[PDB]
Image (tube, rainbow, N blue to C red):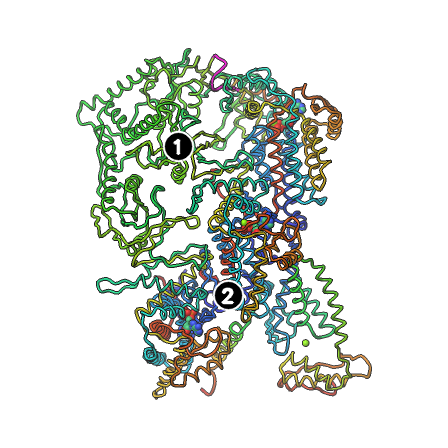
């Protein structure tokens, strides 16, 4: 080895060794992630070094939680991480397609064929596949039913049946709640809270906010019916002067005067709040809730509670925007210009206590543009799994709304796309037809893995589905209960079009780049 | 006891003679052999592992050479010349390494034949002068106004990279970025793509969606949610001074003895912030950009005037914004002027890409800085795309500064080798043999291209030499993908003259430097 | 991990697809190394022992024995090739290549959920058909000197240099024809192979006697 | 031919200390075995005849108790599946307060029978579906098994009878006395408003006189002494201050600037006069007891002694808030004299000695108030801790009764009836789910079996007799622990009853834990780390 | 027992159950009571205990003697605890309590 | 992402101390270099001088 003659402490793989190493790593990753695909996939238990337990079947989460130190695994993991970051779904399919592409490419490379021809065939097949996907997408008006179908198609793969149905209802309702016509959807306005006191099916959607902190003064009211919401970012605690003031007195009376007069600055803002509260509501019928992003010292808390005002302190920064959109007021950084129109309105505010932590509920808003999903479960791992599932569902629904087209699932699109690629193969000049065939066979992995996870046999189910598609022309997928060919569109198994496009692009690019690597070096020491 | 007495300290090794020369030449040859196979349109990529856990999948020679560690000092010299070639012209980093390795390889033959290295060095210098002369003689002019030819040049520069699939888009991006970055002031032409052509990579999406913006794009969000995230024609005001209340430089201390002094001082802090914001507002801006923090009270006073503020932007990003929107960064807003207000930005949008907020100052009219937004499969893919785009922009700048072109695909190598060989017939001294040796050592580029293509080296190279023995055949090279001899007037693969000149100069001078060396000494401290 | 590892803590066990993958990988590695041996256009190999003895060879069996391998499947394949060499004296490289390719082709279908038993049944049927076809295609012919020369050439050209092979062909055919009784088994123990170290490799010949 | 290499793929890619377990035999059976081991370890403490266990944690702290949740807390459980079952048990403890041993036993039985079903040929999905169907059937049946209701909570004898069963499992020898104590303490709490707060019941443990000498006090007891010289007040008018009993100081910076000799001579005298005026102003309102959360200045103590004011210092602010709730006072942020609304009243405050420790008692004479305290005597700290755990179980049972007033028969009667009904239901369901349903029904036998085993009799005879009597039509007949031979008796008359919510939540959580354990197919354990605990748990 | 690839409790956990465990508890209580047997009555004797620092303590009081002993047996610590309880509540009888408890168990 | 594993097949099955060189660069050029070194070592003793 030339490299080892310079740096003796180096690890090098060259020529066929690099391809063998990369393909072996990809095949191992695919072998591990085969069991995740589909609603019939198997759960995994992931125990960290500290002993924490996770129960997930996500491709990205599983990839993060394996104990793997391989370079090709790192590359595939980064590709899947980008997949999850942008589209939010299709990581297991990403890994499976990359692995099958590499396997099919090696099936020809091992017989003396240069990888460049395979990459050219991959490029041609990718172009044709993108054209076919454009031809096959189903443009639709994203009503509630289609969104529910998409949410089921994701959550059934992420959790079990009835929990999936509950999560579908909650996710679709929340997305439709925060969605503005002809305006991009901001997923930051859906706050995800976790409480750990009830069953997993108790997860629901609250048309308001749930804050993990409550009023710190015992005398403050625990339940306010009609509330005026004041969202502020003003410090109501003692603040030191920036220029190192210090006090100088000559008697105890002077010290008492200086003690009493050092609170005047904060007392002025507290008095402004109290004056606004008195002006807005002259009786005890209505309530006043002050939600502050900064701290409130006990003196200000007592002064506010003497007037029947509920005050929250150290609220999250995003809660300013969330309460502004839900309650409808305005976030204030100063009280100099305080007006009644600056107050949001909430139809119910109450505090819920669970163990050592207290939660505040702000419900019955007029038309909340920001809502919250309250994840409930008896275990921490259940809460984490439900959070991941609802993230996947929210991404899926947002993607479906973003473009009015959705793609049939259950492997139908891959089968039809492979058939189209096979038909188009003769048009490709040269030996790139081998690469086109490899790409089609790699695309056919999804129905194969679905049949495996459902417990059927790959060959019989695949030939049945392919024969049905060729004979009828419909987009027929895999029936995970009977194994027979089945139309995905009619039953309501939908896949995100953007997810499939990203899958094709990323898988083709990463496979082409890996296949062209002929040397692996570790000589930075 | 009685420790031994030495002249030089312990562990001070010394090697001398023919062994040192052979070791240096073999080290250079090994360094060349490391990246020999990464040349041409048929090059295969390499997968490097960083000591910190990173992975560098690249085809660029300079990146590969800078990501490895060596102990032989000749290898260090080779790495240094690769870095020099990368920094000077932008590409040619593996061609120069291969050429230097071949020159040292052919110099070893004379060093083993009782020839002093000084004679070889003199012959090499004469040969380098004649190569410069021939390269300038066989060049062709280019008019920079023709955008099609510029795109073709950039394409011929990037056909050897992983971006050749989207070569057209890449060429358009590089050309537009270089054209916008180009700037002149006080009679000083300036093309500074290092600072004013920023490449931002966001993983995801598709690479076909990557584009160059008529503005800038920074990973920032509004300080306050009430602030507008969409403004049509913003009047941008740039700052590099914090909008908060800060302690003075002097040792200042207060002494409070009256009741109302504490609250008074706090009120003066608030009033100072208010006056600062009023001074900013007097110019009637739309967005305010600061390099330092912005206090919450300042945010309130700015939103009172319907002004969007971005809190903490980097120095380089602020400079790019100043170039793009025509603003001028100021520190004391009481000294703010109308000329410092940045008008020219055609839109300001703050939209969420993935799970992050990004600020767009796009749609500028005549911007002098740009952001290349790259979207792709992952971080390694985007890093390689960024390196290829850097090569493309460097080549575009080299062509813009120096508008001559020379044929590629080894045609220039063969033409210069033939001219050098023909001129060598006039010499009668002993220096002619190393002269011809380096002349034919220049033939390594077409040989490497043929080897990488997978064709037969001996007969193809012999036929190419025979073709170049004719009169009007100096533009005849080799196809890098089909392994056949073609006229580069038809293939269209041309290279900037500056790149070739720098490559030849660096190769010959590295050969000279490593030939001058003997008596290696090592082990001493600092 | 498994039952065996539970009973014996320091036990190495590969189960289900792991064992099949291990065996197929070993066979593929052996095939990959021995591919270059096949045919007269193959490549010489230099084998250096621990003591420093140099041995140039192209034989598959000789290469396998001086291989530095500690794999079980490699041991099994080496024993099969050893038996092939012991009985017939030829075909060791072809043996290893065919075994490796059979395993690779079987894995090509096994990796898609097919049970190996069906593959083995197909192998048995194909072996029966191939034996029938080999019986059909064999060329029965009375062996004069020319045909024996052709066979000896077909072996020695693949073993050694072409001119050395041409010399060895005449040597071996003449020796075999000399020691051969009519319609009786040939005793190769009656051909003494004596080696001397003072001339060129093409000086080897046949002595109609004993040395 | 002497070593087995790691299989190419995931096996070679795995880290050094990592472990990977996949498939039925390698993962599911191992998890079931671990859960069965945990259930067996906790099993012997079930029921009234359960045996205490000496558990010593990593800090050499001795726990002796038969509370399953405490035992699992103090055990260093390492297996992830056992960790999951322990989490389910702790969730049951948090939601209800009793039934943790039931959760553990039911989960263990369910997982053992799940292993049996998988061995005979059923699939994991079929077992999970059958278990869920049977759990739904059990939850439907359970309301029909209610035998009697609480029907009163302001009574003393009736609530004591209700709470006797919950604290008969622990402290089997003497449960009537503890039931009476907890009943009195809870009846003092729980006003006309239906809300009942568990925190309002305080337990102060004083060593020396045996648990039979324990009593309930309407007020609070603090184990410390008074700062002043007054040690007894008969008509306390406590004023509570959350500020230190000292002259208030500037928060910025204090510096006495003296420029003349007169100021230097007069500063201390003026400060003393000011503090005397403040203390006299406090005393003029009638406050004969002062409670502070901070330090007490020497001059403050002197002037409080001069005006005959009892001083009590409470370092913990939780105790300060509880005292404010008890007396009906408000914590003044400053040292201003309290107005008539903020001055709490207690009918007696005095310094007393119980056993060895000195205590301060805020004693009410009425049988009411916001906070009530149970003072526990005993000869050992561990015994008092166990009695405190029993008191917590009784209080949680009272809270559950306030939430839902329905009750079900105990001693395995409800479990046997549920098993019979679920078996009858599964006898009609066709398909492979019938095996899982029948096994779920059979898993209920682990409760009467464990009760009989702990009691020291033959479990099989008890279970057969229980089935015979239940088939006859007696749904309130269960195990009789007051016999040396297997016998059963009607347990509605015996008064041994269980809360409906306890059984409902225990069944739900146990089934959820079992199905969640069954759902796992692969385990990828990372290399163990010796970190100084996760930062979340501190 | 079996290796159990993933063990239930942390490695090194010691468990003892059944009749032998309770008999050993009784024996430990007997051992503790033996340490104060000769301190009872007018003919009682004093005990000298030296700590790690070398300071010796001489006492006829049962509670003090039990406190000085660094008892670590969980069942034996109950005797020390009841001696402390008797000293706290009453102040006399700190030896009779331990003797009576150990005699009951015996 | 910090170590390069051995390629499956012959590379993994090779013994501990064994060395394998294949191809032109790894084998033929190295052998030629070694023979050149030997010839250079003995060269200076050639001839009467
Ligand atoms: N009910 C269903 N019937 C048939 N096929 C389904 C059903 N639900 C999902 N699928 C298919 O199974 C696949 C599920 O993959 P999934 O586990 O979500 O991987 P990822 O999370 O990486 O997208 C989808 O491609 C979808 O087409
Ligand atoms: N289409 C082509 N046909 C033949 N040769 C080409 C072609 N494109 C580029 N080349 C040759 O490849 C070389 C560029 O290879 P590259 O990897 O960029 O090396 P460097 O980094 O030294 O520029 C140039 O010398 C050029 O002559
Ligand atoms: N006197 C009794 N006779 C028979 N069984 C009883 C009696 N008292 C309680 N039980 C039974 O003991 C069980 C309580 O066990 P316990 O140790 O409290 O476990 P957990 O704390 O998990 O409920 C109840 O199910 C009840 O049926
Ligand atoms: Mg998915
Ligand atoms: Mg280049
Ligand atoms: Mg042969
Ligand atoms: Mg209980």
C146 or A249, nearer to the observer: C146
The residue to which callout 1 is attached is A345
Residue B258: name its quadrant: top left
Letter of the chain that mark 1 sits on in the rendering: A
Quadrant into which the C terminus of chain B falls? bottom left
The x and y percentages for residue C59 are 65, 74
Q: Which residue is label 2 attached to?
A: A516
Q: Residue at x 47, y 12 (%)?
A: D365
Q: Which chain hosts label 2?
A: A
- Which is closer to the viewer, label 2 or label 1? 1
- Name the foreground residue: A456 vs B344: B344
Q: Is residue D290 left or right of residue D21?
A: left
Q: Which residues are magenta?
A: D365-375
Left or right? Give the position of B364 relative to B453.
left
Residue D262: percent from left, percent from top: 18, 22
Q: Quadrant of ligand 3?
A: top right
Label count reads 2
Under circle 1, the secondary element is strand
Give the residue drawn at x 36%, y 53%: B217
Circles 2, 1 touching at the beta carbon (< 8 Å)? no
The structure residue drawn at horizontal position 69% and vertical position 84%, both measured from the top left corner, is: C169
């Amino acid at each position: 080895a030339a490299v080892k003659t310079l740096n003796p402490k180096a690890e090098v793989a060259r020529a066929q060794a690099a391809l063998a190493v990369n393909i072996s790593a990809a095949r191992g990753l695919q072998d591990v992630l085969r069991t995740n695909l589909g609603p019939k996939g198997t759960m995994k238990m992931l125990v960290s070094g500290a002993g924490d337990i996770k129960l997930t079947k996500d491709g990205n989460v599983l990839l993060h939680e394996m104990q793997i130190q391989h370079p090709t695994a790192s590359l595939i993991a980064k590709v899947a991480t980008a997949q999850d970051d942008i589209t939010g779904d299709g990581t297991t399919s990403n890994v499976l397609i990359i692995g099958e592409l590499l396997k099919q490419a090696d099936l020809y490379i091992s017989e003396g064929l240069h990888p460049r021809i395979i990459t050219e065939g991959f490029e041609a097949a990718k172009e044709k596949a993108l054209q076919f996907l454009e031809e096959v997408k189903v443009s639709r008006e994203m009503d509630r039913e289609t969104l529910i179908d998409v949410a089921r198609t994701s959550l059934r793969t992420k959790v079990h049946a009835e929990l999936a149905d509950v999560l579908t209802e909650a996710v679709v309702d929340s997305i439709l709640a925060i969605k503005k016509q002809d305006e991009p959807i901001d997923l930051f306005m859906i706050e995800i809270m976790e409480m750990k006191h009830k069953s997993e099916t108790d997860t629901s959607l609250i048309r308001g906010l749930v804050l993990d902190h409550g009023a710190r003064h015992p005398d403050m009211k625990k339940r306010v019916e009609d509330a005026y919401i004041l969202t502020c970012n003003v410090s109501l605690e003692y603040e030191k002067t920036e220029v190192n003031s210090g006090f100088f007195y000559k008697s105890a009376e002077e010290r008492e005067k200086l003690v009493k007069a050092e609170r005047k600055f904060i007392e002025d803002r507290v008095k402004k709040i109290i004056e606004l509260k008195r002006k807005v509501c002259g009786d005890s019928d209505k309530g006043f809730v002050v939600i502050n992003q900064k701290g409130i010292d006990p003196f200000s808390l007592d002064a506010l509670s003497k007037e029947g005002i509920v005050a929250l302190r150290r609220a999250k920064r995003r809660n300013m925007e969330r309460l502004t959109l839900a309650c409808g007021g305005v976030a204030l950084n100063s009280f100099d210009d305080l007006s009644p129109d600056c107050l949001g309105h909430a139809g119910l505010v109450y505090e819920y206590t669970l163990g050592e932590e207290k939660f505040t509920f702000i419900e019955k808003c007029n038309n909340p543009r920001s809502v919250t999903l309250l994840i409930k479960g008896p275990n921490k791992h259940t809460l984490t799994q439900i959070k991941d599932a609802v993230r996947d569902g929210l991404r899926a629904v947002k993607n479906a709304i973003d473009d009015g087209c959705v793609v049939p699932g259950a492997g139908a699109v891959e089968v039809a796309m492979a058939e189209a690629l096979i038909k188009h193969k003769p048009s490709v000049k040269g030996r790139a037809q081998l690469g086109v065939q490899a790409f089609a066979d790699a695309l056919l992995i999804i129905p194969k893995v679905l049949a495996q996870n459902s417990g059927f046999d790959l060959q019989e189910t695949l030939v049945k589905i392919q024969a049905e598609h060729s004979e009828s022309g419909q987009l027929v997928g895999v029936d995970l209960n009977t194994g027979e060919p089945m139309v995905a569109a009619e039953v309501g198994v939908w896949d995100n079009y953007c997810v499939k496009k990203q899958l094709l692009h990323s898988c083709t690019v990463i496979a082409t780049n890996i296949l062209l690597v002929d040397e692996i070096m570790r000589a930075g020491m | 006891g009685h420790r031994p007495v030495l002249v030089l300290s312990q562990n001070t090794k010394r090697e001398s003679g023919r062994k040192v020369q052979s070791g240096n030449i073999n080290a250079a040859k090994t360094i060349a052999d490391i990246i020999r196979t990464c040349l041409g349109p048929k090059s295969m990529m390499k997968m490097l592992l960083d000591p910190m856990g990173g992975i560098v999948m690249t085809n660029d020679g300079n990146a590969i050479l800078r990501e490895i560690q060596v102990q032989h000092p000749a290898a260090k010299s080779m790495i240094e010349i690769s870095r020099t070639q990368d920094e000077e012209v932008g590409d040619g980093t593996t061609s120069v390494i291969i050429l230097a390795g071949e020159m040292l390889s052919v110099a070893e033959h004379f060093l083993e034949q009782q020839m002093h290295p000084t004679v070889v060095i003199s012959a090499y210098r004469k040969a380098l002068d004649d190569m410069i002369s021939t390269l300038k003689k066989i060049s062709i002019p280019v008019d920079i106004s023709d955008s099609d030819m510029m795109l073709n040049i950039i394409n011929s520069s990037i056909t050897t990279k992983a971006i050749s699939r989207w070569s057209s888009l890449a060429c358009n991006i590089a050309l537009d970025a270089v054209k916008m970055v180009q700037f002149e002031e006080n009679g000083r032409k300036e093309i500074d793509i290092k600072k004013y052509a920023r490449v931002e990579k966001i993983p995801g999406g598709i690479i076909e969606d990557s584009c160059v913006l008529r503005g800038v794009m920074i990973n920032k969000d509004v300080t306050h949610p009430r602030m507008r995230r969409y403004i049509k024609n913003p009047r941008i005001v740039l700052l590099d001074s914090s909008l908060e209340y800060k302690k003075g430089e002097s040792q200042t201390d207060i002494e409070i003895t009256r009741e109302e002094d504490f609250t008074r001082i706090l009120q003066m802090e608030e009033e100072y912030i208010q006056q600062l914001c009023e001074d900013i507002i007097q110019l009637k801006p739309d967005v305010v950009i600061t390099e330092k923090g912005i206090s919450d009270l300042a945010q309130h006073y700015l939103m009172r005037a319907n002004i969007t503020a971005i809190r903490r932007v980097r120095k380089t990003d602020n400079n790019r914004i100043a170039r793009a929107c025509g603003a001028r960064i100021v520190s004391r807003p009481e000294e703010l002027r109308e000329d410092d207000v940045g008008t020219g930005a055609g839109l300001l949008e703050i939209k969420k890409i993935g799970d992050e907020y990004f600020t767009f100052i796009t749609d500028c009219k005549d911007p002098k800085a740009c952001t290349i937004l790259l979207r792709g499969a992952s971080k390694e893919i985007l890093s390689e795309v960024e390196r290829n785009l850097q090569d493309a922009m460097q080549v575009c700048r080299n062509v813009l500064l120096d508008p001559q072109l020379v044929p590629g695909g080894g045609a220039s190598e063969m033409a210069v080798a033939h001219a050098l060989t023909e001129k060598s017939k006039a010499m009668t001294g002993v220096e002619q043999w190393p002269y011809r040796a380096v002349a034919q050592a220049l033939e390594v580029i077409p040989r490497t291209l043929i080897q990488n293509c997978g064709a037969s080296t001996i007969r193809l190279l012999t036929s190419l030499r025979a073709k170049h023995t004719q009169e009007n055949c100096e533009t005849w090279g080799v196809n890098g993908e089909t392994g056949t001899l073609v006229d580069m007037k038809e293939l269209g693969i041309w290279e900037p003259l500056a790149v070739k000149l720098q490559t030849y100069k660096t190769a010959v001078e590295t050969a000279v430097l490593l030939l001058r060396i003997d008596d290696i000494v090592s082990g001493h401290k600092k | 991990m498994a039952a065996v590892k539970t009973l014996n803590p320091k036990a190495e066990v590969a189960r289900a697809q792991a064992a099949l993958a291990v065996n197929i990988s070993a066979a593929r590695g052996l095939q990959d190394v021995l591919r270059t041996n096949l045919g007269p256009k193959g490549t010489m190999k230099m084998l250096v022992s621990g003591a420093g003895d140099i041995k140039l060879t192209k034989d598959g069996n000789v290469l396998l024995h001086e291989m530095q391998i500690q794999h079980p499947t490699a041991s099994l394949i080496a024993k099969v090739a050893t038996a092939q060499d012991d009985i017939t004296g030829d075909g060791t490289t072809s043996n290893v290549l065919i075994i490796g390719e059979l395993l690779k082709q079987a894995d090509l279908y096994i990796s898609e959920g097919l049970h190996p038993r069906i593959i083995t049944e197909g192998f048995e049927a194909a072996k029966e058909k191939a034996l029938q076809f080999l019986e059909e295609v064999k060329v029965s012919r009375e062996m004069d000197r020319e045909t024996l020369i052709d066979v000896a050439r077909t072996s020695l050209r693949t073993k050694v240099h072409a001119e050395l092979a041409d010399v060895l062909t005449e040597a071996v055919v003449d020796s075999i024809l000399a020691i051969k009784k009519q319609d009786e088994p040939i005793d190769l123990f009656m051909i003494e192979i004596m080696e001397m170290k003072h001339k060129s490799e093409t000086d080897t010949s046949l002595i109609r006697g004993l040395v | 031919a002497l070593h087995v290499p790691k299989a190419p793929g995931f096996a070679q890619m795995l880290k050094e200390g990592a472990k990977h377990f996949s498939g039925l035999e390698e993962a599911v059976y191992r998890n079931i075995q671990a859960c069965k081991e945990l259930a067996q370890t906790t099993r012997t403490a079930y029921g009234p005849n359960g045996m205490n266990k000496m558990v010593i944690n990593h800090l050499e702290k001795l726990f002796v108790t038969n509370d399953a949740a405490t035992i699992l807390r103090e055990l260093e459980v390492q297996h992830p599946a056992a960790k999951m079952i322990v989490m389910a048990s702790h969730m049951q403890e948090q939601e209800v307060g009793d039934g943790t041993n039931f959760v553990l036993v039911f989960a263990g039985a369910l997982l053992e029978l799940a292993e049996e079903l998988l061995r005979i040929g059923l699939s994991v999905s079929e077992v999970i579906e059958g278990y869920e169907i049977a759990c739904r059937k059990a939850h439907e049946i359970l309301p029909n098994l209610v035998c009697c209701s609480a029907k009163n909570l302001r009574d003393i004898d009736e609530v004591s009878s209700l709470l006797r069963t919950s604290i008969m499992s622990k402290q089997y020898g003497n449960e009537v006395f503890l039931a009476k104590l907890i009943a009195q303490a809870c009846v003092s709490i729980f006003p006309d408003s239906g809300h009942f707060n568990v925190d309002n019941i305080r337990v102060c443990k004083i060593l020396g006189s045996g648990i039979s000498s324990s009593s309930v006090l309407h007020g609070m007891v603090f184990k410390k002494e008074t700062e002043g010289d007054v040690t007894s007040v008969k008509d306390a008018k406590i004023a509570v201050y959350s500020c230190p009993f000292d002259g208030m100081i500037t928060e910025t910076k204090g510096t006495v600037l003296i420029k003349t000799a007169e100021e230097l001579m007069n500063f201390s005298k003026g400060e003393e006069n000011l503090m005397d005026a403040q203390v006299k102003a406090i005393a003029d309102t009638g406050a004969n007891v002062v409670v502070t959360g901070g330090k007490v200045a020497d001059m403050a103590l002197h002037y409080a002694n001069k005006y005959n004011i009892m001083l009590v210092r409470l370092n913990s602010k939780w105790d300060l808030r509880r005292l404010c709730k008890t007396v009906g006072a408000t914590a003044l942020p400053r040292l201003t004299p309290p107005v008539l609304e903020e001055m709490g009243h207690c009918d007696s405050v005095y310094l007393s000695e119980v056993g060895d420790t000195q205590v301060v008692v805020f004693k009410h004479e009425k049988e009411d108030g916001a906070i009530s305290t149970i003072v526990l005597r005993g000869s050992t700290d561990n015994l008092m801790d166990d009695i405190e755990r029993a008191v917590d179980d009784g209080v949680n049972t009272f809270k559950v009764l306030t939430r839902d007033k329905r009750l079900v028969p105990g001693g395995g009667a409800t479990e046997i009836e549920l098993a019979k009904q679920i078996t009858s239901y599964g006898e009609t369901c066709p398909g492979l789910e019938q095996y899982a349903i029948k096994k779920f029904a059979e898993a209920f036998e682990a409760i009467p079996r464990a009760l009989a085993e702990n009691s020291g009799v033959k479990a099989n005879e008890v279970i057969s007799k229980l089935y015979a009597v239940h088939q006859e039509g007696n749904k309130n007949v269960g195990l009789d622990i007051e016999a040396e031979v297997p016998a059963v008796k009607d347990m509605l008359e015996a008064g041994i009853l269980d809360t409906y919510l306890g059984k409902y939540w225990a069944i739900k959580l146990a089934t959820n834990a079992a199905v969640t354990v069954l759902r796992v197919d692969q385990i990828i354990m990372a290399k163990p780390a010796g970190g100084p605990k996760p930062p979340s748990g501190k | 027992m079996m290796p159990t690839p993933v063990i239930l409790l942390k490695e090194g956990t010691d468990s003892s159950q059944g009749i032998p465990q309770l008999v050993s508890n009784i024996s430990a209580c007997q051992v503790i009571a033996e340490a104060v047997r000769t301190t009872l009555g007018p003919r009682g004797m004093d005990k000298l205990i030296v700590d790690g620092r070398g300071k010796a303590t001489i006492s006829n009081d049962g509670a003090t003697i039990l406190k000085l002993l660094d008892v670590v047996h969980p069942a034996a610590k109950t005797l020390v605890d009841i001696a402390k309880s008797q000293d706290a509540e009453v102040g006399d009888g700190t030896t009779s309590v331990t003797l009576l408890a150990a005699e009951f168990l015996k």
